[PDB]
Length: 512
Ligand code: MET
Image (cartoon, rainbow, N blue to C red; front, side):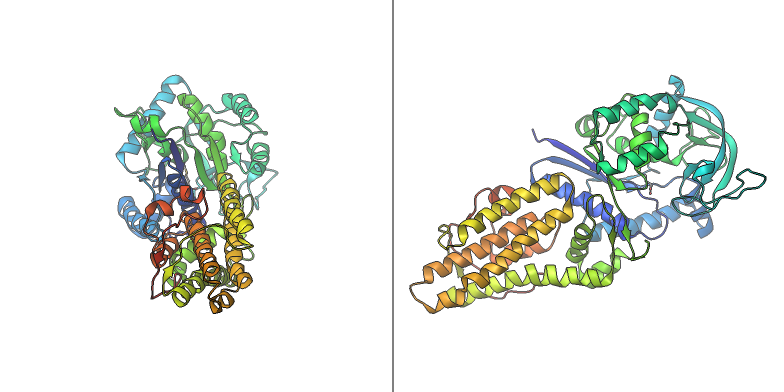
């Protein structure tokens, strides 16, 4: 049948206001999903939210709300954003749903019966704003009193770390140390980019995998341990199983789970890769489940010094295509990006409105002026330049694909704009207005317009994963009504338009 592809975003904390960093994660996963659906995969694209823990409970407590009411309100605004960004997620998984909660209970009960989980006491440091256990030496701005650390802050968030000293269940992750290390030997590509692996092994595995405190006795808000209801399951164990619980794991019908698991990519930001690539594999080893194929960790979007840009405000001012394009263009593979408002409008006005927007405008006007809208049919590479430009178009599809497969979206986008820049330069080289003056050069004039439009069609098809408005408008104004000419397989042979087409007599702007 159709080959499967399962890609996931991380499930986010409904903590206040989403930022372009979480919008990047969701837009990039959508670009993957849309891209894979265009290639003829059976794609499942999952996102969701992380609703349990002390952090969320304190936020709802501070708000003067219940957890569900506070959550329901935050989740409503999160989903408002995804609908506006136009995310093609096949499912949305909330951890407060019983279809999730029952899987967390059964996974915990099972690990207890295996002897993988045992009871004890965690003493040490914890950042509730990070939901992360820390050791003495990991603390930032530590407090020494008679040679002993009695306080500090989190290296991630910079928030004050608090002392934990309570009864807790421990997942024996220490005994999977060599098996996880052997997994990295067999599968060195597991973490993409590979540059993020060695720091993560050096910081988190080398000093010794301490057993992970996987339950909590102090707070109330979370999945309760069924054998011992006073214990509430740790948020990160609770959260991690959303990728399998949403597929119907440990239900009557695991047909969706057998189909889509293991996941092809787990997409995330670089500060939560330790959970998905140490704990998440060790956990699946304990459940005897096949591990993920990739864990793509992307960089941050900095603010000219360090890390309050609202996606909503960008979409309202400059449109969706501008905001979506900017995100994928300005964050490279293995790098962080800077948001500057100057950089944003340059990318919106010069790349979209001018380079692509005015290419379609220049082309359609010349077809209206020189042929009254009747765009001539494609014959062949009749012009001197056509042969290497047609090869350029097929190399653009080739190079783009290689960039899309290795998760280099800014390089694929720069490759496509190289081609759009060429197509604009083709107007300057051919000088169609000089061909229009001669009656014997009508055949060559029509060749240039047909190549102009076929170059645009190539670009619009390649931008369908990235841009959800522009290609669709481009086909309407050009009057390309065949939905097969909007697919990737129509780019295999240049010059698909063999019958003439009546283009629009009222060309309107593609971009706002
Ligand atoms: C299993 S992914 C959990 C991610 C977590 N909610 C975060 O915001 O970092």
